[PDB]
Image (cartoon, coloured by chain):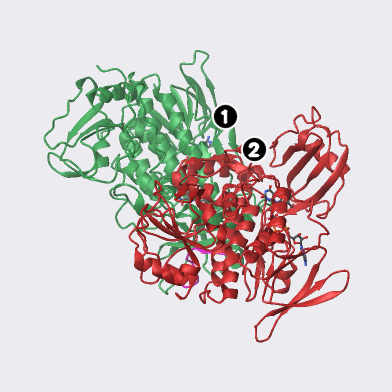
Chain colours: A green, B red
Amino acid sequence: EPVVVVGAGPAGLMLACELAMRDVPAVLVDIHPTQRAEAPAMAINAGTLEMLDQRGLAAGLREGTVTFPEVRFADLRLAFEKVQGPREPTHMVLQSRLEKVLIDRAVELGVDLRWATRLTGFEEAADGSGVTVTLASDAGEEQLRCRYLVGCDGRESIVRKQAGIDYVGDDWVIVRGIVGDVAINREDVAPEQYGLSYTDNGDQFLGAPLSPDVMRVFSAEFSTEPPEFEDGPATLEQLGDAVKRLTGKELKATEAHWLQHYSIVTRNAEQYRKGRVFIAGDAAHVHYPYNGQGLGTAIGDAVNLGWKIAAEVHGWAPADLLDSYHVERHLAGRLACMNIQAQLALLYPRPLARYMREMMGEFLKFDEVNVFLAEIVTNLGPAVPIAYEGVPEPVEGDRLLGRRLPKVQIKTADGDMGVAETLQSGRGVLLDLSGDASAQEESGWADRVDVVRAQPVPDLPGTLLLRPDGCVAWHDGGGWGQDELRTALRTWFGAPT
Amino acid sequence: EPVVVVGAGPAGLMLACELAMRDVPAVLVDIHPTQRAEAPAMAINAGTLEMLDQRGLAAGLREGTVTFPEVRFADLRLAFEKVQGPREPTHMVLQSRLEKVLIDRAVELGVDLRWATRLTGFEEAADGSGVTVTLASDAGEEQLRCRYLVGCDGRESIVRKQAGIDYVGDDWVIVRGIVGDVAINREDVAPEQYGLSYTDNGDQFLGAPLSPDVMRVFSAEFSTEPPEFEDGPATLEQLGDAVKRLTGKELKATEAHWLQHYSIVTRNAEQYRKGRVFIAGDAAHVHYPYNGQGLGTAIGDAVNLGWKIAAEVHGWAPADLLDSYHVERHLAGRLACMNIQAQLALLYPRPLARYMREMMGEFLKFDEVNVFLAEIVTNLGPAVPIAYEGVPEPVEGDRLLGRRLPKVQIKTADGDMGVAETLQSGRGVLLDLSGDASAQEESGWADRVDVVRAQPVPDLPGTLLLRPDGCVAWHDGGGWGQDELRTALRTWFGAPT
Ligand SMILES: Cc1cc2nc3c(=O)[nH]c(=O)nc-3n(C[C@H](O)[C@H](O)[C@H](O)COP(=O)(O)OP(=O)(O)OC[C@H]3O[C@@H](n4cnc5c(N)ncnc54)[C@H](O)[C@@H]3O)c2cc1C
Ligand SMILES: Cc1cc2nc3c(=O)[nH]c(=O)nc-3n(C[C@H](O)[C@H](O)[C@H](O)COP(=O)(O)OP(=O)(O)OC[C@H]3O[C@@H](n4cnc5c(N)ncnc54)[C@H](O)[C@@H]3O)c2cc1C
């Protein structure tokens, strides 16, 4: 019986995929007649690449795409090379190219996607075993009965609203500006300034030439006084004042494909799950767009929740399972909101930025804060907490537990392999890196866990257990072994067959 | 040929002692008729205690006074137990009690101390051979010819302004309050108003009793619009009003001995020195009063600068030694201003504080952050940078170089003492902790440096060289030896004789 997703944005597309690949029905609604043209995001950080790699959604959208190597906290530099294991630079695949990869993958799996469809209301069952939901369409109002409802519908989520869920947060300034694309003149070399510049008050402009003709525009201006223009469709010459004030120069590039005023607000819903309803992505948290974190956490919420919903659809999910979704992702929600606000504080207000910058100068000389911030801003981090009653804590400096593996090559049967492609089935993975296949395969979970035998791998333990979202749930590099291994599968994977 | 010190707070008093204990003629000018009563500070931190221990001024202030062993950042806890070596809790010593012992020490060491005397100006001679100063007593105007002019005359330093050094800083909020001592019953006419009362805005109220009839009172209020009253004498009715809104009740007020309006800005002088004119304490840097840093840096300033000036007077100072006053002490002012302001940003405004508290919450899980901040707010504080030509920077992290040693016993054949006590002669110390007098003392510097032969001390190297301000300029627990020590001696104590 169906599961309803609202929003064909990055969070909803991925989650519908996550579901359908596990043979669970999923209907995905969206107001847009077609895939939207206003996908502002351009970047994807390493953390999000690993999650796409886990579904084979990233080979291909690497290629031709160029990468940038720094990872910055405001304009300060983080020492990303201090993160454990080999990782990835941020890649420059447009959000629209990624939404389509997710669209045409969603339906190939079997997603009932409905463009031009808005959810306008929903009601829990007095039983509680379902949620009746109503949908406005060109054809008129339908009323579908679903088994779980997930609102991936952005900052103004009605799913979040009608569910009773508070949207906590606060801002001390309002950043605002415009984002979009403008034509160029072509055959002749283009001129002007366009590299991301700052002014002495925190104001930023960036011309990003996507491709010979087309260049994306972003500006960001700080002030307490409420935005002038109420966040709509803009016009090209609201924009050209925009740059002239900030740049000094004039725009001089005709026509504007799509443009969008925006304003920021920092929010993080206090509950990610109420009963049978869930919220995810910008529906659950929103903030100034830095480091690709909004797209990072959106994809990450879906991956987290998808396999967990399927698990209880097929009746093996421990009672704990779906509550762990709120636990692990409200933490990532909190850490994202937090660090982006901390980055703003180094730009505005200028009396505050002055001392916070020096402050961060002092912290960034410490290796733990460089590594902590780097895992956070690239969505490698929030390590989902891993612990089991009774079992001895793994000694001390273990940074594999509750994280996804570095981008390391696995050598198995035939064909070397990225570690994250072992999760493309959708199941758990027990990694055996002995080189001879010695580990005891606890067969009772073989329906939900795949074993993969391979040669040992530098600074990685002899064997590892992965949840279907890729988080390392067990390994034997520390004190752990087969006994701790079992209680780890009882958790996260339920009762053995 | 005198040295003129303007201002008899901690800074100027402490320096006049540093100058007079070394037989440098010092004349210390203040305008008060007697020692002031407007000395609000109730606390002395561990770094200030060590610097006073170096001159026998700490014991005596310590007996009978309370300690509390928590070092806070804003209102969070700092893991002070992670700071190297044994050290001290903050002791609750009253500013006027401290100033009294330094006025005492000054008059016996022969400082010409002048209450009711104002410095109205000064000029640097064209050649530069001296400064001529002008002092304004009731009798008239002495025009005094002196050798160096040190302005320790407080936040509104005439010396700084007339020397034309810019006073750098900014604030996003203006903190205002009043402070002083009311007379007022104690038993049960202090309710809520006992101990500090952080409220549901950044605003605090501190009520601390001295004797059962007098109480010291402190208020600190955050607002985005200028202080109602100019800084100055204030009325007790004005305090009654302020207490009611903060504590919620009213103080059964009897009489006011002294109370004062205060506002807070944050500034760091750009140059603590302009050739023959130095500045120190509040004239060099000011900020919100936290952790005792205003007092620590003030005393720290004088301990650094008295001995360098004395060396120049005595003619053995190296050429670049007084320029290290600015280098060493501007950094310490920088970092005090920086982290005070950082502490304030966990209080106000409340949107900023919301996330900056979560942020610091994450950073204080790290040892290097706890130790760095705890060191600075206790004025154990900025390690003085120690490097020498030829000598290559020692790879391992050294917690002793550039810092005053931890509170350890050192046992001599003539008796035991704490290590800060060996610097009481005013001279540098060569600590030979071998137990055998195995260290080869460079007899050249025998007149500027004392050898102290003591028993080995756990977790300290076998030999150490202390500059007259207690700072470790050399030790042999890394790779350094007799040649590096000879380098250290030339750069800090000058030519060998
Ligand atoms: C100017 C700007 C620049 C940005 N730059 C970046 C960047 O460089 N890198 C990055 O990672 N992130 C960036 N972001 C943020 C990032 O784009 C968002 O986090 C991400 O697109 C939101 O993920 P989402 O799918 O949950 O929300 P959305 O993108 O808002 O998708 C929600 C979808 O649900 C639709 N919907 C369908 N039906 C309904 C219904 N009944 N009710 C409500 N909605 C419905 C909505 O129309 C929408 O299409 C930027 C944001 C802005 C404003
Ligand atoms: C409300 C308030 C609360 C405080 N709370 C604390 C606390 O909790 N803990 C702490 O450690 N410190 C506290 N302080 C003080 C802080 O430490 C100061 O930095 C320190 O007292 C300043 O020392 P100083 O000697 O450089 O300047 P000052 O103490 O200001 O002394 C300067 C002296 O020079 C005099 N003078 C000025 N101009 C002239 C002139 N031309 N000629 C002659 N004399 C002149 C002045 O009258 C004064 O006597 C507080 C101060 C205030 C106002």
Q: What x and y, as percent, mark residue A293? A: 45, 46
Q: Label 1 sits on what residue type?
A: Ile
Q: Please name whichever residue, A395 or B60, is drawn nearer the observer in this view of the structure.
A: B60
Horizontally, is A83 left or right of B97 in the view? left
Relative height, residue A170 to residue A158 (above, below): below
Q: What x and y, as percent, mark residue B208? A: 73, 38
Please, what is the dominant secondary structure of the magenta stretch? loop
What secondary structure is marked by label 2?
A: loop
Quarter of the image for residue A388 reads top left
What secondary structure is marked by label 1?
A: loop
Residue matched to label 2: B66
Q: Please name whichever residue, A399 or B156, is drawn nearer the observer in this view of the structure.
A: B156
Quarter of the image for the N terminus of chain A: give it: top left
Of the two numbered discs 2 and 1 in the rendering, the one whose residue sits closer to the viewer: 2
- The subunit carrying tag 1 is A
Quarter of the image for residue B131 reads bottom right
Q: Is disc 1 on the same chain as disc 2?
A: no
Residue span colored magenta: A191-199
Is residue A143 located in the magenta-colored stretch of the structure?
no
Q: Which mark is residue A165?
A: 1
Circle 2 crowding by C-alpha within 10 Å: few under 14, some 14–19, many from 20: few
